[PDB]
RNA sequence: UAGGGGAUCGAAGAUGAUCAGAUACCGUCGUAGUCUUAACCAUAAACUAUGCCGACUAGGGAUCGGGUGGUGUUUUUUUAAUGACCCACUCGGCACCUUACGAGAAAUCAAAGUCUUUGGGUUCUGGGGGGAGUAUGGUCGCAAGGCUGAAACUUAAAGGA
């Protein structure tokens, strides 16, 4: 029930049971590999890849069609990105919020929400400590985000 | 009810009940092989777009994304699968 | 999931959250400061020696009237100044001023008995010879 | 969360059965539970029970009798020594006769009277009557 | 370090001889040993130049009685360290345990290069300082 | 506490009323405050005056949120589609009725039930009435004040239904 409010939401996907094939789809596994790796340099994020893959071509999930899970694949190919993608939207949100707090120090709602958010991050950053996918020590630093992306 | 086979109930009672409880979960959304009229091409679109996809290349448009299901244009056979 | 930690490693937080609680329960209050030695007359006791002053008269508390018989004492210790109470008859008579008397409780702890107010002790002996006798005439006094 | 499994389903089974449901559905399936029922069943307290899989942690139907009186989960899962169960029975079994306290050793996700014939003891999850 | 004299006082493993008169080949000695108690006596011991008497293997300290571990906590001492042993304890009343810990002062040789975190086996010497008793014997890195 | 805001209400203050008095009730105005930024305080009948985890007992009919099934109700557009709807079912609520097998001093209580047939897990609290949540120390606060918390003395009742 979402970890920050009074809210008990339910809504995901009801991956379907079949492990193998769609059958109705008859194109190749190699085929979508190529496609993702096509996409990536252009300017991707794995989250989006699937969406784009789903809405246009055969696919159903990368997952059936290959024995991997997008990322894995980009990582083999070296396109993983320096960041674990979900993070690179949170930090972003930081900058994008803090900035707004500073045009209008007379705003609380916003304030709180910022924190809240500093925290999403520390916890998620503690995990992508733990498991060898952030060089140890990483710590998040409020002010260092604006030449980390632009 | 003092009792009931909940294994297999009616087909009814599933169609209406919520995706995530028919027992074994399964999706509602499903895919839909589109001839824009001009070309014969056939693009494999999804019932819930999010994207409008273009058809194959003709640059055409197709199906807008809304709350859940595309609204597809006029031309489109949209045979399901 | 009532208000207490329950799983396995929840020794630590229990031997504390009774040891806190106990506090308030009045008794375990007396026994840690324990009061008994500092406060009150007998300190960590049961009986004691004292020597009388006046023969005071204390009327009643009221559903009662009852003008009872009390004596101030001088103990032979903290010195408190105490009153105390006499049984039987007049009983008063047999406690002739600046005499030696042997005091004890009133079976109530602290507290304060029946129809008497700030009063908390009885006169058991005198001179050390009963009262019980110096009212059923098994002895007499020097 | 759901912080613990066995519990959750058990409680619903003493809240089906009370009302006279002839059965149950319960969510998160374990081994633990499969084993748990397989004890209960041997002893005459439910029947059949028709796993169902869905590639997930999975759902389990448990057809009734209307016998069950009562099967609470205990629940830290304490430890226990042989000669100690002799304290439990009479602090949560109506009689003695009967009605099995129930525990987890090494064999065994198996009650105490069978435990004698094995002479073993460890931790004590649920109990039936 | 590494440079061996460094401790004005010169260094040697006592009772060792070499023979500047007599053909010298190999020039140096060494004396080493093999703890024992199922151990492996590493090769940075019969190789390593360093001295240290308090060395298990290159010196005069026995190992007898505990064998034990755990988790390093701090290392900041010129040839010596510290261990935790996070353990469990069974209060008979709440029937439950607590996470308890004692720290441990111990010698150590240059044969091992321990950072913090590492799992670590140790021995138990005669006494070796003010506190100090065990001597590392086997590291368990990443 | 210092800036901004200062419509309306409106302690304080002023008033006219009533009244033996009326510093109150009634009426009309009224700083301060109500509002906000930034910082304090941490109390309340903060109230279900009912600690939470759990597990089990006995019936109902409502409702909010989900989910499942019924060639289910309309929508009509051509059949569907969904959607509202009906009903069937369930899991999770927020409550309610009815019993009393139980419990209670009772009033009442599906929990205040499973307690002299006395024991599932654990944290706080009280032990007559006042004196008094004062005096004191110790501490948090700028202050208002909070949390901590005596005793001497007095008293045969104070209280609940």
Image (cartoon, coloured by chain):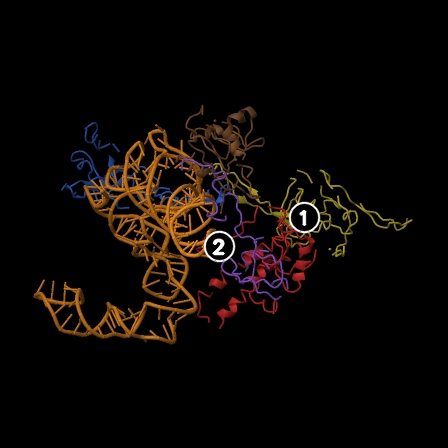
The orange-tinted chain is: F
Q: Position of residue E10 (x, y in %)?
A: 77, 54
Disc 1, SS: loop
Disc sitting over residue A3 in the figure: 2
Q: Position of residue F96 (x, y in %)?
A: 30, 45
Disc 2, SS: loop
Quadrant for the N terminus of chain B in the image: top left
Asked if residue F55 lies left or right of residue F10, the reply is right
Instruction: Work out whether residue E80 can be spotted.
Output: yes
Between C18 and D40, which is closer to the camera in this rendering? D40
Task: Give the total number of marks visible in the rendering.
Answer: 2
Image colour assigned to chain E:
yellow
For mark 2, name the chain: A
For mark 1, name the chain: E
- Badge 2 crowding class, 10 Å Cα cut-off, few under 14, some 14 to 19, many 20 or more, is few
Image colour assigned to chain B:
purple
Between A13 and A84, which is closer to the camera in this rendering? A13
Disc sitting over residue E107 in the figure: 1
Image colour assigned to chain C:
blue
Is E42 placed above or below D67 here?
below
Residue drawn 79% across and 47% down? Answer: E46
Residue drawn 44% across and 39% down? Answer: D12
Between C30 and C89, which is closer to the camera in this rendering? C30
Disc sitting over residue E26 in the figure: none
The red-tinted chain is: A
Image colour assigned to chain D:
brown
Asked if residue F121 lies left or right of residue F62, the reply is right
3D distance between C-alphas at marks 1 and 2: 48 Å
């Amino acid at each position: 029930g979402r970890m920050h409010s009074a809210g008990k939401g339910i809504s995901s996907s009801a991956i379907p049971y079949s492990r193998n094939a769609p059958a109705w789809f008859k194109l190749s596994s190699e085929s979508v590999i190529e496609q993702i790796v096509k996409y990536a340099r252009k300017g991707l994020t794995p989250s989006q890849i699937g969406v784009l893959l789903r809405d246009a071509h055969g696919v159903t999930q990368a997952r059936v069609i290959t024995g991997n899970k997008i990322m894995r694949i980009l990582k083999s190919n070296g396109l993983a990105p320096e960041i674990p993608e979900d993070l690179y939207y949170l930090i972003k949100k930081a900058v994008s919020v803090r900035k707004h707090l500073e045009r209008n120090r007379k705003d609380k709602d916003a304030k709180f929400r910022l924190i809240l958010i500093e925290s999403r991050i520390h916890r998620l950053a503690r995990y992508y400590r733990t498991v060898a996918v952030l060089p140890p020590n990483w710590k998040y630093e409020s002010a260092t985000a604006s030449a980390l992306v632009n | 009810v003092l009792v009931q086979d909940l294994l297999h109930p009616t087909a009814a009672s599933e169609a209406r009940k919520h995706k995530l409880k028919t027992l074994v979960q399964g999706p509602r959304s499903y895919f839909l092989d589109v001839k824009c009229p001009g070309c014969l091409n056939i693009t494999t679109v999804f019932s819930h777009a999010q994207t409008a996809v273009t058809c194959e290349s003709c640059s055409t448009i197709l199906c807008t994304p809304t709350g859940g299901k595309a609204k597809l244009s006029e031309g489109t056979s949209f045979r399901r699968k | 999931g009532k208000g207490k930690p329950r799983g396995l490693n929840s020794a630590r937080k229990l031997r504390v959250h009774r040891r806190n609680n106990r506090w308030a329960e009045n008794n375990y209050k007396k026994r840690l400061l324990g009061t008994a030695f500092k406060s009150s007359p007998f300190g960590g006791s049961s009986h004691a020696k004292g020597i009388v002053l006046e023969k005071l008269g204390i009327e009643s508390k009221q559903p009662n009237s009852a003008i009872r018989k009390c004596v101030r004492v001088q103990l032979i210790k903290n010195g408190k100044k105490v009153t105390a109470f006499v049984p039987n008859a007049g009983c008063l008579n047999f406690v002739d001023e600046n005499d030696e008397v042997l005091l004890a409780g009133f079976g109530r702890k602290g507290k304060a008995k029946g129809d008497i107010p700030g009063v908390r002790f009885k006169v058991v002996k005198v001179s050390g010879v009963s009262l019980l006798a110096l009212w059923k005439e098994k002895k007499e006094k020097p | 969360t759901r912080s613990s499994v066995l519990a959750d389903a058990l409680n619903a089974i003493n809240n089906a059965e009370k009302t006279g449901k002839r059965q149950v559905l319960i969510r998160p399936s374990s081994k633990v539970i499969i084993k748990f029922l397989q004890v209960m069943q041997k002893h005459g307290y439910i029947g059949e029970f028709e796993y169902i899989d869905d590639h997930r942690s999975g759902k389990i139907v448990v057809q009734l009798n209307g016998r069950l009186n009562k099967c609470g989960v205990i629940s830290p899962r304490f430890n226990v020594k042989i000669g100690d169960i002799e304290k439990w029975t009479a602090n949560l079994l109506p009689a003695r006769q009967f009605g099995y306290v129930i525990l987890t050793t090494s064999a065994g996700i198996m009650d105490h009277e069978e435990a004698r014939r094995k002479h073993v003891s460890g931790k004590i999850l649920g109990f039936v009557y | 370090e590494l440079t061996v004299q460094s401790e004005r006082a010169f260094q040697k493993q006592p009772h060792i001889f070499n023979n500047p008169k007599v053909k010298t080949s190999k020039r140096t000695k060494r004396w080493y040993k093999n703890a024992g108690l199922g151990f492996k006596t590493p090769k940075t011991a019969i190789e390593g130049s360093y001295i240290d008497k308090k060395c298990p293997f290159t010196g005069l300290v026995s190992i007898r009685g505990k064998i034990l571990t755990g988790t390093v906590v701090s290392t900041k001492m010129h040839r010596t360290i510290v261990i935790r042993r996070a353990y469990l304890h069974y209060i008979p009343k709440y029937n439950r345990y607590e996470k308890r810990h004692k720290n441990v002062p111990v010698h150590v040789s240059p044969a091992f290069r321990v950072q913090v975190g590492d799992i670590v086996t140790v021995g138990q010497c005669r006494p070796i300082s003010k506190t100090v008793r065990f001597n590392v014997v086997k590291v368990s890195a990443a």
